[PDB]
Image 1 (cartoon, rainbow over the protein chains, first blue to last red):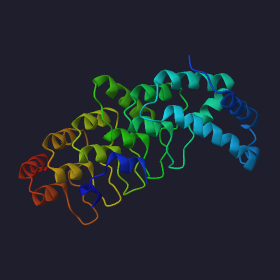
Image 2: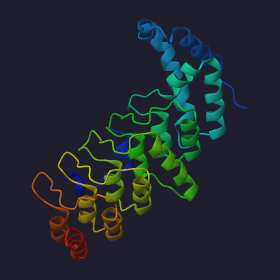
Image 3: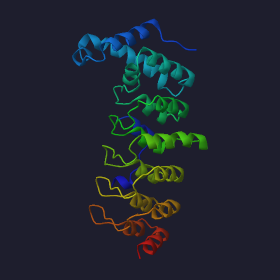
Image 4: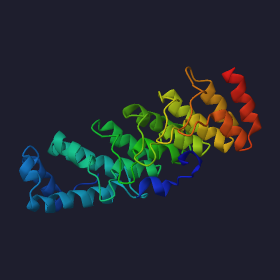
Length: 15
Length: 244
């Protein structure tokens, strides 16, 4: 689930 | 004071004469012009080492060509769908973020190819001084704090909560974030906090007028059931207390 996953700064910036 | 190169000033003037003619603007030859603009603008604005006085000087020079040329260039997106606002937020270059906001023509809600807006990027950006947080809150007030990312429909508030960023959560709530928005899977910020065991963030969310602890995700899980299952009995007791 998205609510459990970690998102990094690089993942926000680049696809 | 920094000045545009001859070639850059030239490209700006060409844009000025063409900016109102859509089909010229899309012409293949005009693209070489637009590529010059994009290249030089991202060179000066978007590296971690960008110099705020240089960005300021460039902004002033674009506006002197035309306010419409300023609006066009500072809203350009690169091949990643990123604007200078995306890069300057990601780099925590908040003096440059402030210059872009103050130009008063930024589209702050632009999603990059990854699917995120600059407000979402800010939710994970380093903020080392309370004065930088003032710029972050100005950004939050210039765009849609409730926007949902193309990836999973998450909000900035969910992102901040998932990283345990109490500072950002307080900022987003103060700037009008809706605590009850659900992502594509039906998860709320409160559910995100329950997964991670972030006690103080749970209290902050529960303290918001209209916080709805009863919401279920698409499988019928609640913040309370999530908390117990993730082994965070203290949050579960907190949730129970608030719900009853």
